[PDB]
Image (cartoon, rainbow, N blue to C red):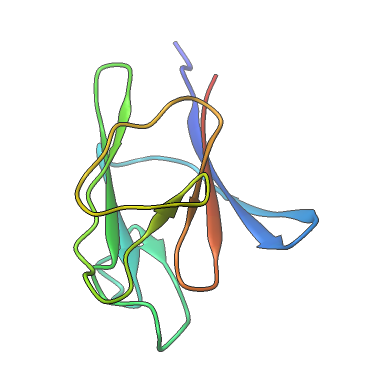
Length: 100
């Protein structure tokens, strides 16, 4: 009853940071408080990226053009499908998508 799809935000290069439980089927990234994944960095956009949770999959929805979100060290031109254990990286922060 606990699929527990957690989004772990790596604090810095080398260690695990605070976790982010998913209460909403839609995850949004950015400075704006409206973002499920609040980020405190002027460079990051209000609606920088978005993870849309599906029956069994998490889907990224990048809006930023100049500074696009990144996955596994790969630039994201448009929304893409994510695999369990995939790593998402923005301008200076990283997020982990784990589906237990």
